[PDB]
Length: 11
Length: 126
Image (cartoon, rainbow over all chains, first blue to last red; front, side):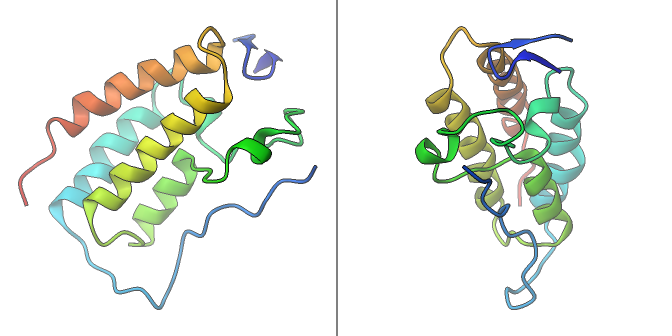
């Protein structure tokens, strides 16, 4: 899933 | 501000055939990439509304994703294997054009593209 869409994922 | 309709995946007016290269693209290439750890952002059209990317489709006029490619293969939408390969290449190029090279999505696309090339290099003879 995204922390910041495209920029940093959270998984 | 809205998402466009997704790419067409079925067309009863196009002729249909099954070939060993198309079967490989579905059962080997698509399947391998789909199961990859980094595949999830590529398994469906980019949802620019949900992801808050208001300029995505102002920049990307030829969207493509692996969910579309899978359904196209399953619907015998492609007559030539090169049509399918081009859709994979469009998917990767869109990602490189829209995003920045340090973005996690680009690192993910690069790893998937490496795997794609490894499998395409083994595409069977027709």
